Image (cartoon, rainbow over all chains, first blue to last red; front, side, top):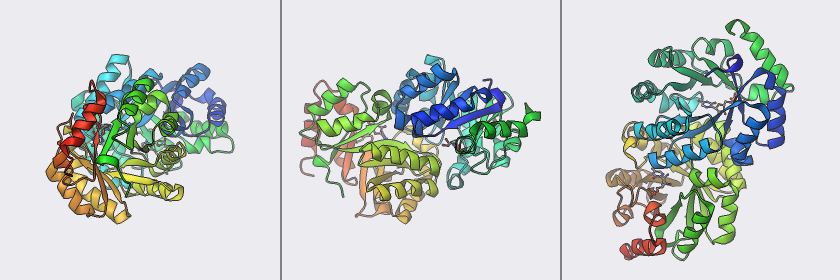
Length: 218
Length: 218
Ligand SMILES: O=c1cnn([C@@H]2O[C@H](COP(=O)(O)O)[C@@H](O)[C@H]2O)c(=O)[nH]1
Ligand SMILES: O=c1cnn([C@@H]2O[C@H](COP(=O)(O)O)[C@@H](O)[C@H]2O)c(=O)[nH]1
């Protein structure tokens, strides 16, 4: 996956007008948008097609899929029907639940991103101690796309070690949650950025600024 | 605690609006509590919650297995309660801050959180099971009153009941299709969640009636 400027916009505004306007304001800087439940539950799944119509951007559905295999399959099918290119799936519920997602993605020509360790403090309680094993499970299952924590570059580096340089790794927690764009890109292929851009007085200037700060990394 | 008719909660995971409405209407005399999840919501929109309220005299539990960072969890809960859900199901494995975020919104908005501890599917053994007692104890410490545990593992369901105490409200999934027995499960759970055994039956009303007849003494 070729992400323009190594920068993925996390569009978590919950109003269609604002979401479309802000995304439009930064469109020259991105070609990949992560859409999650805040926007989808507020405005409907049709918003995904609307983003593709307006911006032609690729869409990663950050739905943290975390159900039993049967329900996971249905979730993935509904999501890809709406035009998502990829979906983010939790690994904590185990291999069968991940495989269910991999099956649908293969069937519809899409990608699964396996979330291994999360960026927030609560991730330390249970997720962090399982994270390496979750990553090895991804490797065993043939997962090629992963998500790890910008807020813990040592943990992000370990995740990269496990999955290898061939796998694709994106990372959340940049900016608002404290992660640094350039440091995160030592290990991740692309950074996810939400509030630092979409809550900024001038989102285009914010995006431009982040890109300037990583200009030597492409 | 919520008064669940016949101790039976329908898991309405049909993805077609017409079918979902038909089947739910057919079993309405037996069930006043419906669990609506992402298969239906991502297919038909959050307005499906409104439609169920209008058509049936049923409480709505949104099974969204909320599993994000606190900031995103808050937004998901707000959107879900705004749409008319009485309660939402939240994962504990992302840790205490993530759960607290949901509890805070539920308190502010006058609704309820159900904490999912151990899941019913085979993959739950890989990571969730080993964390489940601690997740339950965490729920108790956070003041969580409503919980979800696995019908498929009576021994684990019994232990979860012990941890949360007799005053807490416990519902349980994995009954029927996944192998759980209604009667045994109700030794420990206040109510059972049943999906496919009802909604895939030639006669869903007869299926629900049969389940209820099998537990009449309870
Ligand atoms: O471990 C994770 C996984 N996903 N996200 C998601 O990435 C985005 C981060 O946005 P932010 O830059 O505003 O913090 C949000 O959509 C959040 O749900 C994280 O923050 N951390
Ligand atoms: O641990 C859990 C938690 N939730 N569910 C949910 O409960 C329902 C079970 O439906 P079923 O009776 O068709 O198996 C489905 O909506 C599934 O997502 C489980 O099955 N197991």
